Amino acid sequence: QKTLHIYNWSDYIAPDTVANFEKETGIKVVYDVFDSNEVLEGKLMAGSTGFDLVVPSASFLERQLTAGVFQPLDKSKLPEWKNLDPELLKLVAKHDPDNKFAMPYMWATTGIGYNVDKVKAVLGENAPVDSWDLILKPENLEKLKSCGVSFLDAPEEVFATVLNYLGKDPNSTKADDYTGPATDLLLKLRPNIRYFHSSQYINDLANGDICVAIGWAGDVWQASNRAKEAKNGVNVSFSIPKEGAMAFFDVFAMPADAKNKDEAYQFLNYLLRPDVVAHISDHVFYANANKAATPLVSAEVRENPGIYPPADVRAKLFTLKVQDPKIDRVRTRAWTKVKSG
Ligand SMILES: [Cl-]
Ligand SMILES: [Cl-]
Image (cartoon, rainbow, N blue to C red; front, side):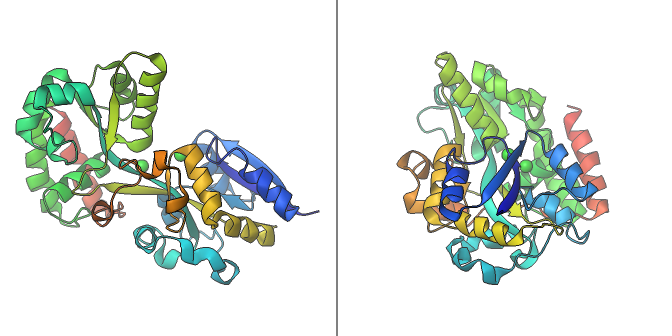
């Protein structure tokens, strides 16, 4: 009679996680998947989804903090909550103050995807692939222009990255920071950027038509794996630069009208086990938010600096704060001015 209804991304869990949880607890888990965040968000805002646990983005959960859509997590029913990284917890608290509604599941960054061979051919073995200097210094973008440079069509993320690169507050609330120095540097870099797109760079990296790109980690790993599967000889790598990068989190959350709260808390505690989430990370190739699980992650994933960055880089990570409307308008018009080049 024990029932638990979960809604998650497809292939966003280890193949045997649900089976092991069912065999250990005796609960019958109804595990449904979605291939697009629009479906999950529309169902959640429509209400009465019938799900006990869902996996939305932390930004959507932040947008839905006062709508009564999610249930505040009873921290007393989660003793292993201490296993979570306090640094990543502080990072996600900006989307969820006091970590009230969401348990961080996996996370990724907005970093640099690049062709190793072409970059080291036009910039040498000393190419600063571990720094935004590779793509945010005009002197290097001039030498990289011939092999192809692409930027995301995401003004918020790109502007936050540029503000962090310039030493300013990555989520500055001053419009002068956006219209002034950030716009100045972006317009200085513009003549070397081939296009602004948030999806074409995947296949363009896989085929070698683009050699350096601002990209989300999952997209760059998909491009590199596509190149590997094609056996085309294109070596695509992803780097979280040393100056820091924007981080984004997927979270487990409990809808307010969940009928199986006990089983949901049991599943959350199961996910808080280091070995469980470490196995999940071994399968999905994403870094999890469980510190105690880090030594248990496979050396293939744990020792990848583009997935598990060192402490000095993790201390420079940041999340995207929701901006006041005037900042949004200034950002959009500045991005329109930048893209006109
Ligand atoms: Cl995802
Ligand atoms: Cl994102």
